[PDB]
RNA sequence: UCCUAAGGGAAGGGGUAACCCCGGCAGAUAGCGCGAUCACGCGCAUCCCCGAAAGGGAAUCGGGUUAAGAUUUCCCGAGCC
RNA sequence: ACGGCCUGCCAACCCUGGAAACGGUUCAGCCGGAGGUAGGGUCCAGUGGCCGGAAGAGCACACGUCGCGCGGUGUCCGGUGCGCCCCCGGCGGCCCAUGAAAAUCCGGAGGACCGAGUACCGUUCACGCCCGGUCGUACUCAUAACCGCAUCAGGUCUCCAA
RNA sequence: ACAGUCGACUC
RNA sequence: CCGACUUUGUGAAAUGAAUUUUACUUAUUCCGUGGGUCGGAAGCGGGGCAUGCCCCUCCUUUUGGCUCCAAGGCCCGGUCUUACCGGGCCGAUCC
């Protein structure tokens, strides 16, 4: 006990050698990291036009989770789950000579198929991933949806959409039909979605995004207007 | 005609600098946290003669701010530094000869050397033997400063730029006549192959605009335009006047 | 031919602190300077009242 | 992070696991003892070397080296070499001087092969 | 043979119609290293190769011997790295 | 060559002491209250001395033998120097000239981590064992072996030097 | 401040 | 050498019915590092003569020394179960 002592180190500007603290800010990153961070910086600096600024305005967290509950209910057929449907009709085709199957109800996907459906008005709801690259694949969707009068939402996460259909990226989904036991709970999210996006289009098409300067620049601005007062 | 001696220098074949026994670049320390917001003590270990340069060079051994090792920096000697001297580097280092300070810490009239131009370019002005710059005024609404350079030219420089207090050592070196082709040759051997120089008037026209003629004479105006093509821009480039300077003309 | 397996260690070293690298007159002055400045550290702290 | 430099992380690699060997045949030993000791040189100079220095003088393969020369003189002749020296003759062939341990007699070996 | 000098070639990149031209331009850089493998931890800083039978440099001396090798290459003795 | 012991130049360093009536010293310098002279020392160089190597070798003689026989003796003593060549030491001098780098080797600063005494951890110690790879290696180096259409009074870098 | 031994040279 | 178009975007004023001036930072150019401390706000002290509420400082001036791989405190967890290893924060202000 007596031998134990305190030896304070003075971490001055010419004192002890400083220890291992967090230098994550100043790390020199690979060029891949560097350009992708400067990418979001430049997309913030520049003035995003209204067509692209309609994105980053996504469906809420609660509304998105509630909608994804239903999208999880109506998932497509797996591959292992698609072998059995064709393998067990063997008795019906070899012996029965009858087709007894009925229409299943699944979510539709793929940009071309969903655009065909939307232009033929067989789409009850359209789900657009906010983060599609290249964006031109989904820039034109909101206007098409709005002016063909289809409820559309821009949810967050093309990978999370891709999971619904078991592909790596999905970039668009749509519901065309729902089972009779879930119409009310579908039309509630339909009311919310229609109120949120399809009505506010006619005023967000004039709103410019982007132009939010950096933290330091905003700090000097906040310094400047105080002096201006 | 053929390529002129003045054009031939752009390749480096026989005109590169003789840099075998030089002791490395003579420059300040990397500008960092310590040197910006405080002071660092460096001990001067030896003042060495750098071949090819008129000024002595002071090797200074700092301690690395954030990792356990020394730093042998190499400064341009300011007249007065001696081995064992502690030179202080940073903002709040006192103003004494050999110390290096930003111009925000040097009062008007102070004599300085090895000045930076862009904050951190490690010292570029007033480095030749016996040259200094006088810090004239400070504008704190811009964070800028003014200096009188050895040429008499007056420059505006950022105020956060470092500068060594004092003047470069070896002053008055050029005061001594060399008296000999020998001394001239040994001067230029360790600098570069730019000596002896043959008067173009004693050349042939194929290699110099002045050459040729039964007598030795230039032939036309010895002053050429600023825009003259290379190989013709030879003589007195874009001269504003000529003749021995008298009166205000030499001010 | 200073290699360990070519000279005897007593013939390669000098038995003091800093021996073989610093002479006696230099090491003596380092001892004195280190002691004295260590003393001034704490006299300066005591002056800090 | 602590250091402000980014280094390539330590990945894991596999050693080669070929699905088919790019060479099927096992390479035959083309520097066998018989290519590596072509024949004992029998000029009068090597003849005198036989008794005066207890050494056999061979013409050996140009790609042989002292290690293989001893290893080969051991497998043939059931002898061993205390030392071996090699030179390249001007004519192109390498000539090797093989000095025997004193347990073995160069005359007896050279008579069991037939030189004298 | 090894190491560098002046210097030379080069991986990524920049140029080029293409051969070819530029090496510090900074790039997850060529190479990673060391302690541990009964595995992992720590470091990575001016980051490659080539370049001298006159520069630097692990170590050998004496006596013999052949028609022609050796002064220290073979033999004899004694050493060294 | 190598190994041991001894010697310890010129410089460098140590201990005691305390210098003016200033001394010490060089061909020349120069050094000293920051410690001279003086006394005693430590270290360094060596291509220095002795012994081992090693007289068994070499040489010169002197005999006597058929045929790389053999036997015998000697291989000592001083001194000299503005002497020649080579190297080293330490001074001094010139420079607007300050006169390479690395491989390699050694030393040190620090001390995380570690161990027995019916025994275990080290050891840069002595001795002992094994192995040392590839390529050049002859000869001229020139009034005849290189180049000049040649066995050309030409030209071509060095070391030894009575 | 003398005695003994030696001394290669220079003027 | 200079002129125009192009990369070349933002908003602001003053003159004419385009012109010079400006402001911004992300394009662009340049400079510096082993991208090692940038911006704002706290706090430790010093100025108070509206206790303001605005300023000035960051624990190194010292003699040719040395500084690394944390001491210290608190909170968990594993354990002999009556004897001991791994954790987290502060030390090293936050955002
Ligand atoms: Mg010249
Ligand atoms: Mg001149
Ligand atoms: Mg002239
Ligand atoms: Mg002429
Ligand atoms: Mg002409
Ligand atoms: Mg002329
Ligand atoms: Mg010793
Ligand atoms: Mg050989
Ligand atoms: Mg090499
Ligand atoms: Mg060599
Ligand atoms: Mg050599
Ligand atoms: Mg032998
Ligand atoms: Mg004495
Ligand atoms: Mg000796
Ligand atoms: Mg000297
Ligand atoms: Mg030979
Ligand atoms: Mg020869
Ligand atoms: Mg010829
Ligand atoms: Mg010919």
Image (cartoon, coloured by chain):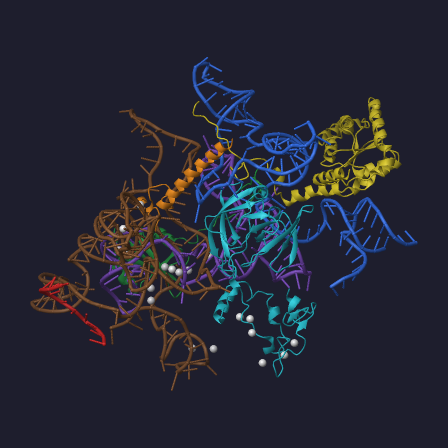
Chain colours: A yellow, B cyan, C orange, D green, E purple, F brown, G red, H blue
Which quadrant, please, contains the C terminus of chain D? Answer: bottom left
| Residue shown at 82% from the left, 21% from the top | A181
| Residue shown at 82% from the left, 28% from the top | A103
- Percent coordinates x, y for residue B214 in the rendering: 61, 84
Question: In this orientation, which residue lies closer to the viewer: F91 or A208?
Answer: F91
Depicted A5 relative to depicted A20: above or below: above
| Residue shown at 63% from the left, 76% from the top | B210
Question: In this orientation, which residue lies closer to the viewer: D82 or A45?
Answer: A45
Judged from the image, the quadrant occupied by ligand 5 is bottom right
Residue B213 visible in the current orientation = yes
Q: Is residue A17 left or right of residue E21?
A: left
- Percent coordinates x, y for residue B71 in the rendering: 50, 46
- Percent coordinates x, y for residue H11 in the rendering: 82, 44
- Percent coordinates x, y for residue A127 in the rendering: 80, 33
Question: In this orientation, which residue lies closer to the viewer: A118 or D1?
Answer: D1
Depicted H95 relative to depicted D99: above or below: above
């Amino acid at each position: 006990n007596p031998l134990f002592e305190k030896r304070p180190k003075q971490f001055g500007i010419g004192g002890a050698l400083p220890p291992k603290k967090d230098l994550h800010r100043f790390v020199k990153w690979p060029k891949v990291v560097r350009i992708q961070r400067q990418r979001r910086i430049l997309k913030q600096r520049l003035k995003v036009p209204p067509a692209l600024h309609q994105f980053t305005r996504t469906l809420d967290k609660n509304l998105a989770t509630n909608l994804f509950k239903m999208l999880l209910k109506y998932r497509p057929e797996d591959k292992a789950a698609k072998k059995e449907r064709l393998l067990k009709r063997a008795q019906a085709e070899a012996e029965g000579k009858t087709v007894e199957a009925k229409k299943p109800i699944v979510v539709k996907y793929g940009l071309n198929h969903v655009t065909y459906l939307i232009e033929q008005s067989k789409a009850q709801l359209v789900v657009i991933a906010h983060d599609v690259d290249p964006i031109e694949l989904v820039v034109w969707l909101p206007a098409l949806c709005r002016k063909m009068e289809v409820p559309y939402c821009i949810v967050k996460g093309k990978s999370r959409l891709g999971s619904i259909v078991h592909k790596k990226t999905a970039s668009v989904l749509c519901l065309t039909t729902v089972k009779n036991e879930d119409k009310l709970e579908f039309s509630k999210i339909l009311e919310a979605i229609k109120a949120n996006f399809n009505d506010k289009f006619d005023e967000v098409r004039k709103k410019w995004g982007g132009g939010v300067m950096g933290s330091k620049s905003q700090a000097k601005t906040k310094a400047r207007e105080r002096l201006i007062a | 005609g053929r390529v002129i001696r003045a054009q031939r220098k752009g390749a480096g074949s026989v005109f590169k600098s003789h840099t075998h026994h030089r002791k490395g670049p003579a420059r300040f320390r990397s500008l960092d946290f310590g040197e910006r917001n405080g002071y660092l003590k460096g001990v001067v270990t030896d003042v060495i003669h750098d071949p090819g340069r008129g000024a002595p060079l002071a090797k200074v051994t700092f301690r690395h701010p954030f990792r356990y090792k020394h730093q042998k920096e190499l400064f341009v000697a300011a007249e007065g530094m001696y081995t064992g001297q502690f030179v202080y580097c940073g903002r709040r280092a006192t103003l004494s000869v050999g110390n290096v300070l930003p111009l925000r810490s040097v009062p008007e009239g102070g004599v300085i050397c090895n000045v930076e131009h862009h904050v951190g370019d490690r010292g570029v002005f007033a480095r030749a033997s016996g040259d200094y710059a006088i810090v004239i005024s400070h504008n704190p609404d811009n964070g800028t400063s003014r200096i009188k350079l050895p040429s008499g030219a007056k420059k505006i420089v950022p105020s956060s730029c470092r500068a060594m207090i004092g003047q470069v050592a070896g002053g008055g070196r050029t005061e001594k006549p060399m008296l000999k082709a020998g001394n001239a040759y040994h001067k230029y051997r360790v600098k570069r192959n730019s000596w002896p120089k043959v008067r173009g008037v004693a050349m042939n026209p194929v290699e110099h605009p002045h050459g040729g003629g039964n007598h030795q004479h230039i032939g036309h105006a010895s002053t050429v335009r600023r825009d003259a093509p290379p190989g013709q821009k030879v003589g007195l480039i874009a001269a504003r006047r000529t003749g021995r300077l008298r009166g205000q003309a030499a001010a | 031919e200073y290699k360990r397996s070519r000279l005897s260690r007593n013939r390669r070293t000098v038995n003091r602190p800093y021996g073989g690298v610093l002479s006696g007159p230099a090491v003596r002055e380092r001892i004195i300077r280190a002691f004295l400045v260590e003393e001034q550290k704490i006299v300066k702290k005591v002056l800090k009242i | 992070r602590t250091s402000v430099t980014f280094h390539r992380p330590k990945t894991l690699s596999k050693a080669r696991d070929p699905k088919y060997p790019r060479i099927s045949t096992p390479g035959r030993n083309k520097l066998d003892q018989y290519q590596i000791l072509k024949y004992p040189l029998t000029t009068e100079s090597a003849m005198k070397k036989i008794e005066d220095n207890n050494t056999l003088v061979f013409i050996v393969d140009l790609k042989a080296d002292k290690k293989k020369i001893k290893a080969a003189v051991k497998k043939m002749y059931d002898i061993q070499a205390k030392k071996v020296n090699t030179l390249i003759r001007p004519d192109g062939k390498k000539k090797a001087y093989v000095k025997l341990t004193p347990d073995y007699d160069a005359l007896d070996v050279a008579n069991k092969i037939g030189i004298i």
